[PDB]
Amino acid sequence: DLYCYEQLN
Amino acid sequence: EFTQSVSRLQSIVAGLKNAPSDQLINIFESCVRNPVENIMKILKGIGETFCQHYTQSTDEQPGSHIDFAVNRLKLAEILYYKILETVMVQETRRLHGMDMSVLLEQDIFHRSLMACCLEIVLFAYSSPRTFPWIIEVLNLQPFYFYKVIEVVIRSEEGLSRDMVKHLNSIEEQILESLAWSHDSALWEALQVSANKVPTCEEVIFPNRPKRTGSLALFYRKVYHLASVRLRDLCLKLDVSNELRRKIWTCFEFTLVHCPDLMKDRHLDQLLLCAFYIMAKVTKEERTFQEIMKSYRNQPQANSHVYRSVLLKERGDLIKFYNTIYVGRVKSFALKYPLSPFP
Image (cartoon, rainbow over all chains, first blue to last red; front, side, top):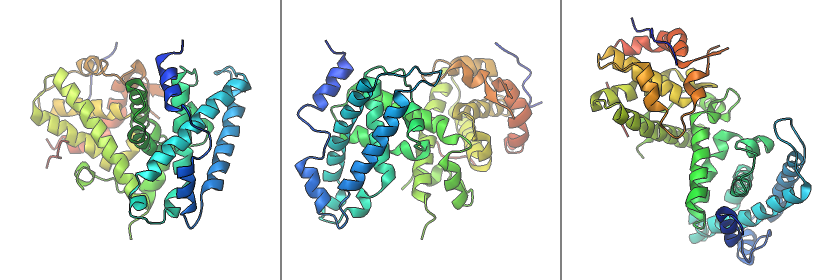
């Protein structure tokens, strides 16, 4: 839940 | 024609010697213990080590001729005695006619001042030897060294805006990363203080463990720097002042109750993580991606800060957040007293 599922760039 | 920085430097040192002035000598001699010989020895030691590194090639830094080293050195020595005289004259103990022996016998001050003078000269010439080259060469701890910069800026008004900017930049570099390296004297100071990290409220308002004063000043500078950066971020991300105070509270928590997270890392990495996890839990949420595009427009921000981060091995900021930061701070976060914002 508090984890970030975004990636980059 | 000289560049503006070198001509300015030339103006500052005009008519002066790489030896103490008569005025300074008199101050030296009014001391129970006259520092003049030990000061000379420090400059001699620093000068030799500087020349040895300057003239030798490390594979990252082609070596350079000794005649330029000596000219750099000479100029820095002239600056040293000038600034030292200014500092000693304006000193409180001097004005009250009190013996300055203990003041003048602290080696770290003189070494730091001479290094800062060398850094001024190197910068003025656009030297390839980039900070922290000079303090690694001279074995000066970042945690101790940075304190002299504000003294230099105060004591020499002939420094240009660009010179002062540079000095403020390398102070910021120390505050944000360098003083946090695993071998930094910071950890020693925290250690004799029982690893008690001063809270922002404690240091932003006016038989102790030694380095108590050093701890207080360093963290005051750290809290001050981080607040300026957080204020800018909140502005560009247009965040409420209430989440700002919450983000600040989380950041302070990581400095105070998880200080090991800073070891060998960057101050902004903890600040950006504080931003997201707090924006998250309060449902004001902003993506790390937009957090970082807003971050990158800040002067200190370089790609490696959120792209290359120490894990245990390096990864981007997001991987750091997930595998490290969350586990440590989630208890404190999921809990959303708030800290004062400078």
